[PDB]
Length: 48
Length: 48
Length: 232
Length: 144
Ligand SMILES: *[C@@H]1O[C@H](CO)[C@@H](O[C@@H]2O[C@H](CO)[C@@H](O)[C@H](O)[C@H]2NC(C)=O)[C@H](O)[C@H]1NC(C)=O
Ligand SMILES: *[C@@H]1O[C@H](CO)[C@@H](O[C@@H]2O[C@H](CO)[C@@H](O)[C@H](O)[C@H]2NC(C)=O)[C@H](O)[C@H]1NC(C)=O
Ligand SMILES: *[C@@H]1O[C@H](CO)[C@@H](O)[C@H](O)[C@H]1NC(C)=O
Ligand SMILES: *[C@@H]1O[C@H](CO)[C@@H](O)[C@H](O)[C@H]1NC(C)=O
Image 1 (tube, rainbow over the protein chains, first blue to last red):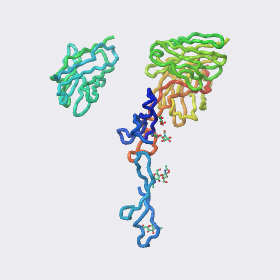
Image 2 (spheres, rainbow over the protein chains, first blue to last red; image 1 turned 120 degrees about the horizontal axis):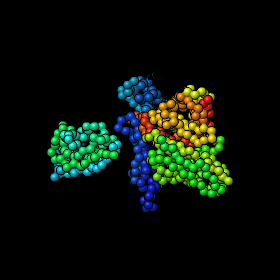
Image 3 (tube, rainbow over the protein chains, first blue to last red; image 1 turned 180 degrees about the vertical axis):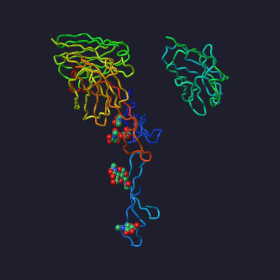
Image 4 (cartoon, helix red, strand yellow; image 1 turned 135 degrees about the vertical axis):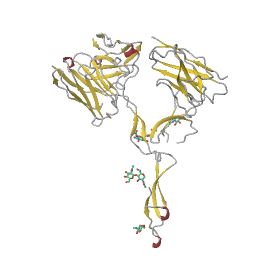
């Protein structure tokens, strides 16, 4: 699951929403530990 | 670990055991939450 | 092509770091590995680093020196730190065997020209004793120290009311907590911090202190003597 | 706004040893580094010592080099300050304060074929952040 939030840095009115500033947990190289990674996901690749 | 339960409804005595509830946790599409699901398993496919 | 082009040479003070780098092409840099030389006057040739292909390991002759690569870019970065007086020589980057065969001793082919690396060479804060101004005016407080405490580290401000516990007002000279209004402002310049207070009232009568924090050096943390504010 | 309790002060002769105890509640003691501030009556504040959240990084003063000891115990939520080689200049009020960075967890324990269970923290980053926002009543230490 993605605890995503909506990006508002140097944004333009035409590109409202779209990019989303997602944060999710992820297995590290050891298969015993969770990181907390973040990424950018367009609104066409994430659903609610 | 299947948590299995003796089936008993409209059964012909002799066919005791055999059919069974077996309720267990199960990974869903999301890899963070588990759905509790149930199924019917024949006695030949489950070992104590 | 095959020849190697190096860059990053220069003069370094003892106790610093460098970013030696070298790049090459020649449609044949997939069979070779790239390492580095070291030739000081009067001595023979040694080795400093060898980024072995087929293992990705960054072998080096000393702990400080480390070789590195980045993506498919045909450039190799030699990072050196904690330099000392002996590490003044002619650093050349050359090509070693596919699996970094015997180095620190070999003399390879397809070598570069080589750059030049030469190495050679209790603070207490000062504050005014006290300040005074009419109510509603603007007051300025100066905290002057050293380069290590104020110049190289952030400064925090504290207010101690008479017969009361101290309270944080300014942290890293540009932010304030929720409970402190915007009437206080802070700035830094060189090794001196300046605190400006506007709309001074009777309730602001307290003793102000400037301090610095850093785990790197023990001289870095230092609390100011203090400034007394009296409202007429 | 959390409560701060300080105790362990008293009147001692020069060269003696003393222990100062600071208590923590309504907040996570493990999640904040400790500092000690000395202030004589009528003079300005003076930093004394600092310890991180884990206690690995210990930092002290030029006036108290090699004679002050600071330790923390997160299990009992207590701060220990050990005094050695007291001098008549040490008579002052000692203030107990905490940090602000609110250190988080870099890693948590996992279970691959599950990945959904809530498991305790494994690795963490924090400490340092020598800014104090909450100051307790403190303790009075007299040397004579
Ligand atoms: C990553 O794992 C952590 C493990 O704690 C999750 O943190 C918990 O999140 C739930 C809600 O999903 C809260 O109810 C708990 O209080 C949280 N626990 C702690 C210790 O913070 C976190 O939600 C997971 N996901 C992300 C994106 O961090
Ligand atoms: C599915 O997994 C959950 C994991 O929590 C199990 O719930 C636990 O059941 C035990 C059995 O008594 C309780 O002691 C725990 O307190 C339960 N956990 C929680 C969070 O409530 C559940 O039993 C599993 N189901 C099956 C069929 O195995
Ligand atoms: C981000 O902004 C868009 C613009 O309307 C909005 O529709 C969307 O819901 C916002 N995202 C979140 C997580 O609120
Ligand atoms: C449960 O099933 C077992 C078969 O293994 C049977 O021997 C037993 O009598 C059953 N009990 C009940 C209460 O149905």
